[PDB]
């Protein structure tokens, strides 16, 4: 009841922003379905979300969480903090641990500086400086490790950072088979949430 | 005695059932006529607030027709019951429901509520009908507490008895092919005429407004 | 367990083995594989004894009770519907012979619940060994005495020829008017 | 266990082609050489299945009974989303790769897991290898009917010879502004 | 129960009004720097353990809710409200916004027998203290300043006499102590009041120490 | 009060049962069901734009079984649907078609449970039941809103009852299809109509032909 | 992972490795395993991240409604026993630490729902290693200087000797009041 | 049941009266000790006739007394037993008198609230441990007390008890005030252990109160 | 008598009729329908000098919003239900809810309450105002009846607004939203007002810009 797909969605908190890029391409075990799929959904407000698990669980999970944020905001007249969003995710996910969602998942939001929540299939959520998931994660994280962090050896100009994202992913298509050549890239600067179809 | 849907009167009448006849007697007329080439149920709802639409007639399939009189709510709900019935039968039997069995089904539905001491009976009589070349037109009227009956055309609602003088000219009412309407528009002296005829392709249809014009302009 | 029964000129005649077995050692010198569902209808089950005592009890009382509840003698096919429906819900073959408004009917009932009307029948380990001798000598409308001797012959063959079958025999002539049992045919 | 090996669908501005062969192999071998796998839910919408048969007629009756209540009219999008929602409910199942298509234009595919999506051209079953890439090769928008149907015919041509299980003749449907047309002719 | 009166008012729930009049009084005043919350403590019998019975409670850490009417029905609604308005925060830290805690309690209060109690829930959640009276009828409303108990019948005017938004929570404390001391028979002491507060900053619910109220008076 | 509900009198005698029997006895649709020698007739008066072609009391509940019904009509269609359900469950369980009394255990018990249980109203309908038995003798039973499997060589139901018992007696002194059906159609004349025999095919229960209505009526 | 806790004179204390790897790969080293429940008690998760996090938050709820109910602080054995009573239905083992008695009690609730009370529990993959140091280097009660060096030390050897745990150190001495907080990077010198 | 136009509940106000006419009971309180003492009348011949009046022990560290219906009291008390055992299971620690007063109150209330159930006919009072006493009225309210009296004519016992009240006192001497307020059902909660006071032991005191009133 | 489980000898149900005797206490609210826009004003009653008055308006979905005027608890329950239902809708079909499907659903809920005896009828009547494509105003009587409208006003002294509605075509000056809203504030005459149509969905101009708009009736 689980199929592997490589949604390679990555998050990346800037000094005054968050950036969430993902390859669009969908694929079966070795054959491409659609050339262009939405691996990223927009949560209703100042935050967005991505995943890379099987697409049924991606779509229905984003659907559910969208229904929950819309219901919450309508019942409370109040757009949720990012934390109640990710926490709610841990809730929903653990509620089904005995038959887990296959969608490993990423959250990116702003608290008013990109507060973030990448995590495992059962809601073991964590904040991070940056995030990757999908089959392309293991490859890119070291690229993201060094470009920003220098644990063994200015790092978030918007231009330089979108560049790091770009080169990281474009390189990721090369070494990985599941990653697709197209990419969406979202940018949640405090004004609003940009979209880019850079590829 | 009159206080129960269930308890019989000393004379065996069910006054509580009997009151539904009053409800329907005051509520808006909803004639359904039958041509010898089709069937035409109609309504004369008598309810700036909108005046443009308030249809009483509705179908359970593109061919069968419903019409009612009485409380709007209960009857709309029974229309939901009939939709779910026709569709259940279509899921089981891979065919559209005969009108007859549906009619008996709604007879049972409406009948059930009468037997229950807490439960309140529906307050709406219901015309249900269909016409095909092979499936000859029939107009089943359902009085609440069962006893659905087949008809050659029955008027129901508030003034039906004074219309029955017109419908009793059912020789002339059967004489028509598509002009029974034009007869009706004077006969009755919001409205919802319809179609189930050969020209209708036997499928139910709201009568066209520019077909409604010849009737109104006829006199 | 052989169990052989066969229709005669006006009455079913059932006959069956009488020796329970645990699989290795015998666990009984005798048993009752000719249960009496009613005066003019009996069952002869073969299989696990436990399941057999069960469904034959539940059957006997469904049939006796239903007979109390209605005028008609519990005509033979109702037992067949009840039994087969019960087995269908889910391990025990049966062979039932009764006589009624129709003919002396006899049925055989598979462990999966399948039913068949039969001229003559056998079930169990001895079934094969009984189909051999039974079929060879059978003729429709035998004198009931021919049933009396034959069914004992095919039973004795289905006894001697199996390790799993042995012991004394018992036979009965289910006339519609009356059952006529005998405890030891041997 | 009847199965239908392939279905394809393609669109151009003036309408949308969608076709399949009528064979229905009952395991190793053909049973129904004339099965009807394409099915018409709506005047502007059809479902085309390519998997186990029973499940397909099941979903067929479901979508229909689901429709008559709404017969604005139920959009192909709502039909598709209801479809995928049903697969994914069932999963936690039915064997098909049903595609919804109709009308501006709309094609959507659904894998057995309720995996689903939307594209200008969709192929289903064995076709994906043996027709899709080829139909990925020559596909162009605003193909006229002749261009398009000659294209899908080239694809089913490659397919019947390469697919293990296909019928020689193709039940075929095109959806147009005028209304859905289920062409009777087969080849 | 829900047999509508010909007059059109619901019967039952309108009979249930009087239960709050049995209530001993309390005066909640939302203010620019917090919510003050006073009530009678002179309700006490001479031999009940002194000041060992609170009208004012705490639904959550940052919610405090004085109660009218029957002590029992209030204890229940506070029980379920504690449960729910806690359960809201099950993994995400934010406690329920006061308006919605109170919305829960009322939306339950709608639908046995109608509750005989009214509440005066207060707290700081949005940048600003909240003050929500819940009528037994399930009608829910945000006063700036308000009182409960039968003494609220005429004591309410006193709020109208003095309530300016602009007060230090201490000024507000003087005010609510004014209005509530007025309706008491005993000269007010810490045994006559059970005041509590939720600060605009501290946001923490805190019953005053008796030394405090003894100090202000 | 005792009358408002299905409970015993101070005199120890049930009320509402009598009232339901007034429902039947003021329904005013009399029906004579007489057994015939090796056959059995069941007749009823079939009582505008209404269709006589629709109307009937007689109804079959299997091939071998047919039950005229009188009383509150909704209850009648319900007790018939219950009857058909009953024969289908018995056949399904046992593989035999029910003997007419066996269908009367279900009819009479289901009709009974209403009597104790105070809520659901007592049954307002009654009527004969006819069918060939496993015993070759034809079987004619009856039932009452108060439980009764009854038993008759002849019966009447409706507005007329034991008024026509003494009238029936005169036929009883003269009691083949000719000979028996004339007793029935006369018994309507004695105190159009619709006649129903089990003996058409001797086991199958069918209402007698429309063309052959008159010939007995004119003989 | 790797969790440690022991009580010297001045209180119970809590120490931990912040690494949280999903398989051979490291998902994160920023992860925090230490969790507070009641204002005075706290627990450390070990084993699965999602289930352990869930049960900790759940514990925070149950304890919170209790604490509201009696309007006071519950004893640590209570908070242990609740997880002992729920986990037995089904995860990951945990350690608890708190103040009700004049001495801080310590506990350890197995995924089996086994409950244990004692003086120097440790858990996680690398438990054994610091767990040697805990008696070789702490047979008996000592000082805060001695203790923070102790736990920092034993965590360091549970960091070197075990590849399944590492990352940052994070010791949390608990005062009779609440607790303190300390975090470190590499300390090989 | 249902509110009268005043908004008072009837079934409750009626329900109290069974307590307002029942055997008196009282409790006197202090630090580590409290004297619970009731009164129950029985036929003299039958010594065993009321071993049931005797003050109940809900837990080794808890104790109860009641006035009103016994038939209802056995029910409430058993629910209390099952509940102290439940809490003592889920916590592995004994139930504080606070939590159990709360639970019992929630029950008596609940029956007054939810439909389908006749309201309780009893008034309870509970001692436990420092040591503190909770009385619970049929309405579902409960309250801490320093001293109180349930039963018929509770007001004479209690308001006369106010005339004599004094807080902490002696383990034995604190008993005497119960009698001075109040054959006798004496029991002493002490050491977080309820105890059935010896019959003979009080007999000396049983004499003096009989005669200090006389002389 | 005295329960909605029985009809009066007149043939009327009293309990449901009492719901309007509830709604008349409620404050008036009024609605106007421009061809592409709908504007709905309320009136927030103030219980004290220090009370902040409650908001009649809500916002069930993007383009749907409502204005209940009856007892508040039933009103909030209908809101929570209608919201949960729209969200169930979108969650199922990745699509906005049909407005009329919603109205039909909520009205089904009313009837489900006003038929069953144990559940009381609602004391509230919604005035839904929205569109999935073209602007609409529905009203739900506290029963199963619901009507579409061009312009609607209801509650307290709504009578002034009703008689006034005749003075303007609902769209006598539809084309400008300011014309519309000025018709709204005339028709009704802190107090609330809200706007929904075309590009901007539901909206509540209760801003101080509205306070500026208030003088425009007298400007
Ligand atoms: C036919 C044998 S066969 C291989 O031809 O099918 C007999 C039929 C039989 C035996 N006894 C009666 C009584 C009434 C009707 C029918 C009867 N059945 C058997 O030989 C069984 C072999 C099975 C596996 C086919 N034998 C048994 O079931 C054992 C009987 C037994 C054991 N201990 C006893 C003490 C006293 C009397 C009898 C027995 N028992 C078991 O096999 C134990 N099973 C294990 C699983 O099923 C339930 C108990």
Image: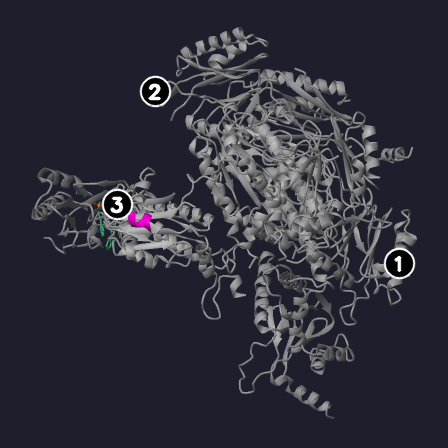
Q: From the viewer's perspective, is residue H104 above or below residue D116?
A: below
**Residue H131 picture location, percent across and down:** 70, 68
Image quadrant in which the C terminus of chain E is located: bottom right
Q: Is mark 1 on a helix, strand or loop?
A: helix
Q: Which chain carries label 3?
A: F
- Residue B158: x percent and y percent? 61, 42
Mark 3 residue CB less than 8 A from any atom of ligand 1: no
Q: Viewer-proximal residue, G99 or G75?
A: G75
From the viewer's perspective, is the residue at label 3 or at label 2 nearer? 3
Can residue E155 be spotted in the picture?
A: yes
1 vs 3, front mark = 3
Residue that lies at the very extreme toward the front in this rendered image? F218
Q: Residues within 10 Å of mark 3 (few under 14, many from 20)?
A: few
Label 3 secondary element: helix
Query: Vertically, is A58 above or below G17?
Result: above
**Mark identifier at residue E179:** 1
Q: Main secondary structure of the magenta part?
A: helix
Estimate how packed mark 1 is, as few (under 14), some (14 to 19) or many (20 or more) residues with alpha carbons within 10 Å: many
| Side of G12 where B169 appears, left or right | left
Circles 1 and 3, Cβ within 8 Å, touching? The answer is no
Which residue is more in the foreground, I25 or A83? I25
Number of numbered discs visible in the structure rendering? 3
Q: Which chain carries label 2?
A: D
Quadrant of the rendering where the N terminus of chain E is positioned: bottom right
- Residue drawn at 53 percent across, 6 percent down: D147
User: Magenta region: which residues?
Assistant: F182-186
């Amino acid at each position: 009841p689980y199929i592997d797909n490589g949604g390679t969605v990555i998050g990346l908190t800037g000094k005054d922003y968050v950036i969430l890029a993902a390859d669009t391409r969908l694929s079966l075990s070795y054959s491409i379905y659609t050339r262009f799929c939405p691996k990223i959904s927009k949560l209703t407000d100042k935050c967005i979300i991505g995943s890379s698990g099987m697409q049924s669980d991606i779509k229905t999970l984003h659907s559910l969480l969208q229904k929950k944020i819309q219901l919450f905001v309508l019942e409370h007249s109040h757009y949720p903090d990012i934390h109640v969003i990710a926490r709610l995710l841990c809730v929903i996910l653990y509620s089904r641990r005995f038959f887990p969602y296959y969608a490993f998942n990423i959250l990116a939001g702003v608290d008013e500086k990109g507060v973030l929540y990448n995590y495992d299939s059962v809601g073991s959520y964590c904040e991070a400086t940056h995030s990757c998931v999908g089959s392309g994660s293991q490859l890119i994280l070291p690229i993201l490790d060094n470009r920003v962090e220098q644990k063994n050896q200015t790092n978030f100009n918007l231009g330089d950072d979108i560049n790091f994202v770009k080169d990281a992913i474009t390189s990721a298509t090369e070494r990985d088979i599941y990653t697709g050549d197209k990419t969406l890239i979202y940018v949640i600067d405090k004004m609003g949430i940009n979209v880019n179809t850079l590829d | 005695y009159d206080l129960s849907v269930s308890t019989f009167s000393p004379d065996g009448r069910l006054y509580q059932v009997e009151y539904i006849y009053k409800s329907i007697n005051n509520n808006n007329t909803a004639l359904c006529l039958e041509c010898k080439d089709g069937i035409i149920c109609c309504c004369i709802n008598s309810n700036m607030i909108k005046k443009n639409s308030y249809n009483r007639i509705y179908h359970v399939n593109n061919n069968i027709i419903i019409t009612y009189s009485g409380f709007d709510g209960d009857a709309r709900n029974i229309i939901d019951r009939a939709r779910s019935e026709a569709n259940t039968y279509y899921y089981n039997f891979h065919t559209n429901i005969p009108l007859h069995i549906l009619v008996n089904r709604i007879s049972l539905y409406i009948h059930a509520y009468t037997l229950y001491w807490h439960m309140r009976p529906f307050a709406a009589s219901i015309i249900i009908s269909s016409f095909n070349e092979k499936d000859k037109g029939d107009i089943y009227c359902i009085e609440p507490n069962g006893a659905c009956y087949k008809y050659s055309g029955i008027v129901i609602g508030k003034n039906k008895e004074m219309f029955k003088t017109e419908i009793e000219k059912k020789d002339y009412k059967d004489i028509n092919v598509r002009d029974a309407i034009e007869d009706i528009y004077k006969f009755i002296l919001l409205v919802n005429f319809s179609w189930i005829c050969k020209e209708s392709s036997y499928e139910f249809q709201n009568i066209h407004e520019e077909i409604l014009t010849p009737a109104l302009n006829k006199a | 367990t052989t169990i052989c029964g066969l229709v005669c000129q006006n009455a079913v005649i059932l006959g069956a083995d009488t020796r329970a077995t645990e699989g290795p050692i015998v666990a009984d010198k005798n048993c009752s594989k000719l249960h009496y569902i009613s005066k003019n209808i009996w069952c002869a089950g073969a299989g696990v004894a436990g399941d057999l005592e069960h469904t034959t009890l539940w059957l006997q009382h469904n049939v006796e009770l239903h007979r109390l509840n209605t005028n008609t003698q519990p005509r033979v096919s109702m037992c067949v519907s009840r039994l087969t429906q019960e087995l269908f819900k889910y391990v025990c073959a049966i062979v039932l012979g009764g006589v009624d408004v129709n003919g002396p009917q006899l049925y055989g009932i598979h462990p999966h619940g399948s039913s068949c009307l039969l001229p003559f029948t056998a079930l169990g380990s001895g079934s094969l060994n009984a189909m051999a001798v039974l079929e060879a000598k059978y003729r429709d409308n035998m004198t009931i005495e021919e049933g009396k001797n034959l069914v004992c012959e095919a039973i004795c063959a289905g006894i001697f020829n199996d390790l799993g079958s042995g012991g004394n025999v018992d036979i009965c002539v289910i006339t519609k008017d009356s059952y006529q049992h005998i405890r030891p045919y041997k | 266990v009847v199965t239908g090996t392939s279905v394809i669908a393609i669109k151009y501005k003036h309408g949308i082609m969608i076709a399949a062969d009528r064979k229905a192999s009952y395991g190793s071998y053909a049973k129904f050489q004339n099965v009807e796998r394409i099915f018409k839910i709506n005047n502007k919408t059809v479902m085309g299945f390519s998997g186990e048969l029973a499940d397909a007629q099941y979903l067929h009756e479901l979508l229909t009974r689901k429709n008559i209540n709404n017969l604005d009219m139920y959009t192909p999008q709502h039909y598709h989303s209801y479809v995928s929602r049903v697969f994914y409910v069932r999963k936690n199942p039915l064997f098909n790769n049903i595609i919804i298509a109709g009308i501006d234009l709309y094609i959507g595919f659904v894998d057995m897991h309720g995996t689903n999506f939307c594209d200008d051209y969709i192929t289903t079953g064995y076709a994906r290898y043996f027709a899709l890439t080829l139909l990925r090769d020559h596909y162009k928008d605003n193909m006229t009917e002749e261009e398009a149907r000659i294209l899908i015919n080239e694809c089913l041509r490659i397919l019947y010879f390469r697919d293990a299980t296909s019928s020689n003749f193709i039940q075929i449907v095109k959806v147009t502004s005028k209304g859905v047309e289920y062409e009777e002719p087969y080849i | 129960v829900n047999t509508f009166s010909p007059e059109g008012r619901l019967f039952q729930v309108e009979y249930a009004l009087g239960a709050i009049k049995l209530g001993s009084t309390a005066v909640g005043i939302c203010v620019n720097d917090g919510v003050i919350l006073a009530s009678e403590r002179r309700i006490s019998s001479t031999l009940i353990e002194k000041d060992s019975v609170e009208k004012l409670l705490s639904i959550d850490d940052h919610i405090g809710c004085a109660m009218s009417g029957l002590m029992a029905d209030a204890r229940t609604l506070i029980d379920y409200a504690r449960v729910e308005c806690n359960h809201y925060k099950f993994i995400y830290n934010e406690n329920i916004n006061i308006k919605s805690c109170v919305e829960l309690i009322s939306e339950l209060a709608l639908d046995s027998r109608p509750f005989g109690v009214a509440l005066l829930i207060g707290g700081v959640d949005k940048n600003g203290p909240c003050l929500w009276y819940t009528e037994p009828s399930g009608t829910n409303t945000r006063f700036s300043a308000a009182s409960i108990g039968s003494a609220q019948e005429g004591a309410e005017l006193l709020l109208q006499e003095n309530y300016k938004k602009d007060m230090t929570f201490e000024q507000a404390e003087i005010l609510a102590l004014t209005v509530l001391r007025q309706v008491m028979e005993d000269k007010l002491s810490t045994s006559n009041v059970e005041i509590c507060a939720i600060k605009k900053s501290d946001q923490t619910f805190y019953k005053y120490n008796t030394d405090d109220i003894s100090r202000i008076i | 009060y005792d009358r408002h509900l299905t409970i015993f009198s101070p005199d120890g005698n049930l009320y509402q049962i009598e009232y339901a029997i007034k429902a039947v006895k003021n329904t005013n649709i009399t029906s004579v069901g007489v057994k015939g020698e090796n056959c059995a007739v069941i007749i009823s008066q079939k009582k505008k734009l209404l269709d006589y072609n629709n109307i009937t009391n007689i109804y079959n509940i299997t091939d071998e079984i047919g039950c005229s019904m009188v009383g509150m009509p909704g209850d009648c269609l319900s007790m018939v649907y219950k009857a058909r359900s009953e024969a289908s469950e018995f056949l399904y369980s046992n593989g035999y078609n029910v003997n007419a009394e066996t269908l009367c255990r279900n009819i009479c018990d289901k009709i009974q449970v209403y009597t104790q249980h105070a809520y659901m109203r007592l049954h307002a309908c009654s009527g004969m039941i006819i069918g060939i038995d496993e015993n070759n003798k034809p079987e004619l039973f009856k039932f009452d809103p108060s439980g009764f499997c009854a038993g008759y060589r002849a019966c009447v139901i409706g507005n007329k009852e034991q008024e026509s018992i003494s009238v029936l007696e005169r036929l009883l002194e003269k009691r083949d299809i000719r000979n028996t059906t004339i007793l029935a159609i006369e018994a309507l004349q004695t105190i159009e109509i619709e006649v129903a025999i089990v003996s058409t095919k001797n086991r199958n229960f069918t209402q007698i032909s429309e063309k052959e209505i008159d010939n007995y009526l004119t003989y | 992972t790797t969790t440690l806790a022991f009580k010297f004179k001045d209180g119970i204390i809590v120490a931990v490795d912040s690494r949280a790897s999903m398989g051979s790969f490291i998902s994160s080293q920023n992860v925090e395993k230490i969790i507070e429940i009641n204002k005075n008690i706290l627990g450390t998760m070990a084993g699965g991240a999602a289930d352990c996090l869930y049960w900790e938050k759940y514990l925070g709820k149950i304890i919170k409604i209790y604490e509201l109910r009696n309007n006071e602080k519950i004893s640590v054995r209570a908070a242990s026993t609740i997880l002992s009573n729920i986990l037995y239905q089904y995860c990951c083992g945990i350690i608890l630490s708190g103040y009700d008695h004049t001495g801080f009690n310590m506990f350890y609730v197995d995924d089996s729902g086994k409950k244990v009370e004692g003086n120097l529990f440790s858990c996680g993959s690398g438990s054994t290693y610091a767990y040697s140091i805990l008696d070789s280097a702490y047979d008996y009660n000592l000082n805060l200087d001695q203790a923070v060096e102790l736990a920092r030390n034993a965590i360091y050897h549970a960091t070197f000797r075990d590849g399944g745990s590492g990352g940052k150190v994070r010791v949390f001495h608990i005062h009779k009041n609440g607790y303190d907080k300390i975090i470190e990077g590499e300390d090989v010198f | 049941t249902v509110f009268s136009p005043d908004g008072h509940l009837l079934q409750v106000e009626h329900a109290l009266e069974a307590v307002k006419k029942g055997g008196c009971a009282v409790a006197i309180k202090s630090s580590n000790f409290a004297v619970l003492a009731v009164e129950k009348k029985n036929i003299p011949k039958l010594q065993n006739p009321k071993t049931t009046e005797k003050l109940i022990k809900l837990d080794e560290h808890n104790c109860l007394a009641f006035a009103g219906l016994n038939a209802d009291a056995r029910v409430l008390v058993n629910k209390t037993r099952l509940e102290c055992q439940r809490y003592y299971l889920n916590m592995d620690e004994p139930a504080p008198v606070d939590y159990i007063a709360k639970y019992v109150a929630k029950v008596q209330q609940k029956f007054t609230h939810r439909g389908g159930v006749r309201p309780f006919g009893i008034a309870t009072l509970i001692a436990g441990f420092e040591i503190c006493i909770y009385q619970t009225e049929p309405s579902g309210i409960y309250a801490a007390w320093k001293a109180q009296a349930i039963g018929k004519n509770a007001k004479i016992v209690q308001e006369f008890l106010e005339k004599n009240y004094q807080e902490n006192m002696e383990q034995k001497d604190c008993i005497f005030l119960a009698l001075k307020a109040i054959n006798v059902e004496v029991a002493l909660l002490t050491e977080k252990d309820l105890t059935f006071i010896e019959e003979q032991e009080i007999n000396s005191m049983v004499e003096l109160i009989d005669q200090e009133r006389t002389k | 008598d005295t329960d909605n489980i029985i009809y009066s000898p007149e043939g009327r149900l009293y309990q449901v009729e009492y719901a309007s005797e509830a709604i008349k206490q409620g404050t008036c609210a009024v609605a106007i329908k421009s061809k592409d826009y709908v504007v709905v004003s309320g009136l927030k009653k103030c219980i004290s000098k220090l009370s902040f008055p409650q908001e009649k308006i809500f916002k069930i979905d993007d383009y749907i919003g409502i204005s209940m005027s009856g007892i508040t608890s039933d009103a909030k329950v209908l809101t929570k239900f209608m919201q949960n239902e729209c969200l169930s809708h979108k969650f199922l079909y990745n699509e906005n809810i049909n407005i009329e499907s919603l109205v039909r659903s909520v009205a089904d809920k009313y009837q489900k309450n006003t038929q069953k005896s144990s559940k009381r009828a609602f004391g509230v009547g919604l005035m839904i105002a929205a569109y999935h494509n073209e602007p609409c105003i529905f009203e739900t009587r506290p029963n199963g009846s619901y009507f579409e409208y061009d312009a609607l006003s209801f509650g307290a002294r709504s009578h002034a607004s009703k008689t006034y509605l005749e003075k303007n075509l609902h769209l006598f000056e539809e084309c400008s939203l300011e014309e519309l809203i000025l018709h709204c504030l005339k028709a009704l005459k802190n107090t609330a007002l809200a706007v929904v149509g075309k590009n901007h969905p539901w909206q509540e101009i209760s801003s101080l810009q509205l306070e500026e708009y208030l003088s425009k009736v007298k400007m």
